Length: 193
Length: 193
Length: 193
Image (spheres, rainbow over the protein chains, first blue to last red):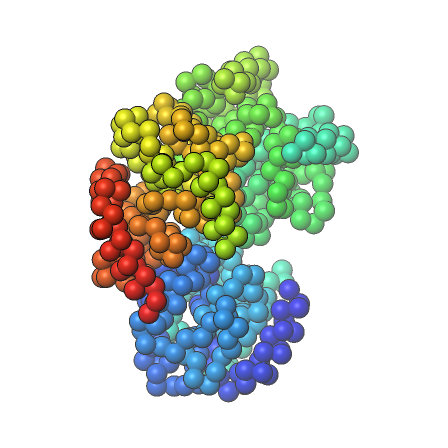
């Protein structure tokens, strides 16, 4: 776990991420990659600073998600091919096993998937919370209902109704260092008790 | 497998389970832990002999289920923290990987989950059957439709319609050594042929 | 991966598969095994050359699927028991982990499951495509929507509406060396670009 934190520091340096804004969609299911990348693509085209890391939940779907990215005409590099995030990279497909912590440790904001699909149900938001990443989930989070509600009650997690709202919320967070600082603070409160 | 049987004998002794009634909810999904623990909590509060082992199907949900237990105000100890079943323990969260056989080998009765949720579908009831544990499933068992029907046809498995009925059935089994002996007998018939 | 290809050559020889027609249902979910085996059983009874390999997606379901086969009165041998395909074998239950490539490498035609059930969603068709196996999927393939559509657009994958249609399509492929040769050709086109 902590090994991932220091590998993230090595990669932050080698990939020159200091002047990139890294947004991550984590543990995604269909049609979440299509919907969020479609909503985000105008910004990835207009603002080369942004880059989206995509971590699909199911490995059998990695090539499927590469095709989604390709069809959206987004420049996409792949962890499975030992690629890195280039200045040119718009989407980094993190198509490997066991490295979710590394990607969260590199992220400015994230979205935890399994939560915009139907029927959905959600995935564990504690991992990005612990790494101080502002976190968005969709409305279908019932497999983690207790924990997500503990965080909604303390204004510690952001709930999106659709893929457009995930992108709104992300762009707002990236523009609002004070709001994101307060969100990470409230998360740390819930996490401690 | 057989290693789990003898470890169960060691733990039965060290945890003084001879005067506890161990009920297990195994391979559970949301909202099965909430629903069954809610139905059972009055009995766990009134009768300190009872203790419920909870084995959620998905490891990413272990901390979620701990929160469910905590909110129900039930005294809960965790395998992941190297805890044991205390006299005070009301719920033992078996939040570890690969040890389902151990928990069934410690159980007086069980419920096999994935079967009260929607759409459900069920999990493998053969494991508790082979270990001579009286077994309850919910009505949504269609992923194991053939095998569960073979056992319903020989009165060898108990079907619950809801979480209240799982608890009724369990309390009845625990009060009825002759009925539970006959159930385990009928299960062994199906298992042999 | 390539190790599986040469093991397939060893088994093709030892099991005398040269005069069998091997049809495979791969990564199946309930009720796909029941539905397809029911549709196929008249042919497996009338034409001893045919044999169906069954590879259920979830290992916990292997004994369940054995029971499905047994109830259909089909002669069934099991990889887990170190069995082989006999002249007498009608269904080979490939109840082992990690060997899907071997079975596709032995197949004349296949069906990729998770795609006739509800709500379905499908599994990765690239694996049989790469091994030159004519491939059928059901209509519920939305987890692989992009890739399956790339193959439908080039007439490179067969879509079945129900279990009867999977069996129609298979029997037609086996009777049509020219059509199956053209299908494998179109698949290889999509795969190259």
